[PDB]
Amino acid sequence: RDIALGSSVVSIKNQALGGSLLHSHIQTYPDGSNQQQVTCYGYKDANNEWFFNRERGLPSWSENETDIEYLKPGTSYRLVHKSTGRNLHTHPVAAPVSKTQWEVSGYGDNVVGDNKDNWVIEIMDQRGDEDPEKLHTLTTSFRIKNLEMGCYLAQTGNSLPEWGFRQQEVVCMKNPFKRDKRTWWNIETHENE
């Protein structure tokens, strides 16, 4: 089953050395924007779960919708943390450890937020033979670009301070090289219905 808008709940794994799972929780940044932390995490738990929602300002996905909408590279989506309902978010705020990159946070909901909540998928590799323009669990590698800031979601390899449970720093990288695997991700788990 290809990944769908709204109904697909996924975990998302980073492909650099020591890369792990995109993660959030209710604790906030002590400096920076003071918004909700986003990290990478080395174990499997429900705080690794995300789903894709429509771009800011369009109708939120509803289970009452009858048609399935498969994710498309190049389309703007929000990436929503399932346990907290916050949107993956960035902005021109320095990251907590990689001070030359941008902080990535969880922000707002279906009402609260703005166009900095819009992200765009770019497929970098398909090892399978399925539709090369769709996302497939495990076998599709992709980058996740913030549309407004132009930067790429990345796990830097830095550990956070104790205030982030010593989890892995996530930033939005400015002008990375295309093959930088800190910016490459895959769907690691997929549950739908």
Image: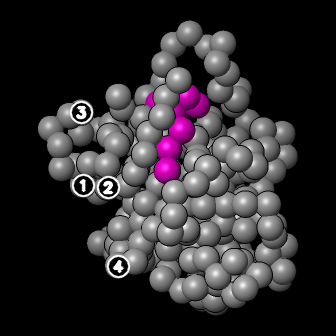
Task: Name the N-terminal-most of marks 3 and 4.
Answer: 4
Q: Bounds of the magenta span?
A: 4-11
Rendered image: mark on residue 17: 4
* Mark 2: secondary structure: strand
Marks 1 and 2, Cα distance to the nearest angstrom? 5 Å
Which residue is at a point 75% across and 49% down the rendered structure image?
84
User: Is 31 located above or below residue 42 in the figure?
Assistant: below
Q: Nearer the viewer, mark 3 or mark 4?
A: 4
Which residue is at a point 36% across and 74% down the rendered structure image?
16
Which residue is at a point 79% across and 75% down the rendered structure image?
29
Question: Circle 2 sits on which residue?
Answer: 141
User: Is 113 located above or below residue 135 in the figure?
Assistant: below
Task: Name the N-terminal-most of marks 4 and 2.
Answer: 4
Disc 1 crowd rating (10 Å Cα; few below 14, some 14-19, many 20+) is some
Q: Kindly check if marks 1 and 2 are in contact, taking CB atoms under 8 A apart as contact.
A: yes
Q: Nearer the viewer, mark 1 or mark 4?
A: 4
Q: Which x, y percent locates residue 157?
A: 48, 83
| Amino acid at dot 4 | Leu
Marks 3 and 4, Cα distance to the nearest angstrom? 28 Å
| Amino acid at dot 1 | Asp
Q: Which x, y percent locates residue 192?
A: 49, 28
Rendered image: mark on residue 125: 1
Q: The N terminus is located in which quarter?
A: top left
Disc 2 crowd rating (10 Å Cα; few below 14, some 14-19, many 20+) is many
* Mark 1: secondary structure: strand
Q: Kindly check if marks 4 and 2 are in contact, taking CB atoms under 8 A apart as contact.
A: no
Depth check: give the residue in front, 103 or 24.
24
